Image: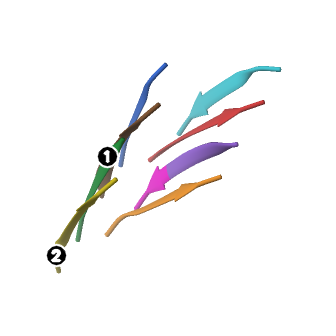
Chain colours: A blue, B red, C cyan, D purple, E brown, F orange, G green, H yellow
Amino acid sequence: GGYVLGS
Amino acid sequence: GGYVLGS
Amino acid sequence: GGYVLGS
Amino acid sequence: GGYVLGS
Amino acid sequence: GGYVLGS
Amino acid sequence: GGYVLGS
Amino acid sequence: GGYVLGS
Amino acid sequence: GGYVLGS
């Protein structure tokens, strides 16, 4: 799977 | 921000 | 089990 | 486990 | 801030 | 600034 | 994976 | 300030 996070 | 947890 | 995504 | 990204 | 992409 | 943590 | 941070 | 890119 995959994930992307931003801040 | 962001977080992801798995179990 | 499971997954959680938050901010 | 998991990941967190913040500022 | 920033960004992260993973699996 | 920014930080990223993993576990 | 990859991450990028800025400050 | 600055920037960092990693894996």
Q: Is G3 situated left or right of E7 in this image?
A: left
Residue found farthest to the right: C1
**In this rendering, is residue D3 above or below F2?**
above
In front of the other: label 1 or label 2?
1
Mark 1 vs mark 2: tell me if same chain. Answer: no
* Residue at 46% across, 52% down: D5
* Camera-nearest residue between A4 and B2: A4
Q: Is C5 situated left or right of G2 in this image?
A: right
Distance from label 1 to label 2 (Cα)? Answer: 17 Å
Query: Badge 1, how many Cα within 10 Å: few under 14, some, many 20+?
Result: few
- The quadrant in which residue C3 appears is top right
Specify the label residue H2 is tagged with.
2
Region in magenta:
D5-7
Q: Secondary structure at mark 1?
A: strand
* Residue at 65% across, 52% down: F7
* Residue at 53% across, 49% down: D4
- Does residue A5 belong to the magenta stretch? no
Give the residue at mark 1. G2
